Amino acid sequence: PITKEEKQKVIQEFARFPGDTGSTEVQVALLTLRINRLSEHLKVHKKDHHSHRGLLMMVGQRRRLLRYLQREDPERYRALIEKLGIRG
Image 1 (cartoon, rainbow, N blue to C red):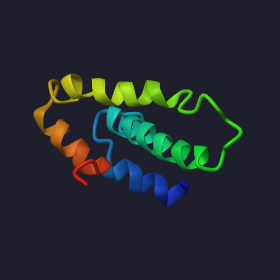
Image 2: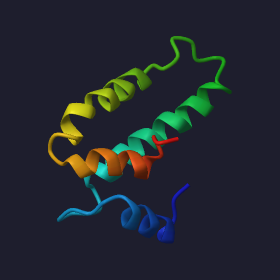
Image 3: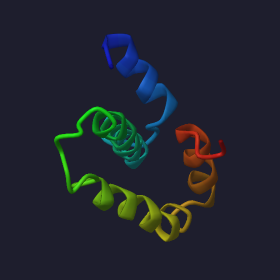
Image 4: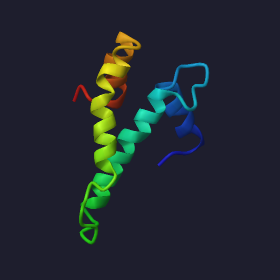
């Protein structure tokens, strides 16, 4: 859950563009946070069959991100995956 300084934390961590508030980094960050949140949501929501309803779209955009993120900046590939925590 974000807050005033949590926003500042997310922005100082991820977004570093002329508009570091709605930058790709923060949006993929929120896309990944949404996936995680929704997965823990679905682990409670047993009433929601056809699960991963809109999570498949995000998983798809996350795997599509490969030839986009890495291509428009080689550092952003490896460093946004570092930021998100895809390194493990």
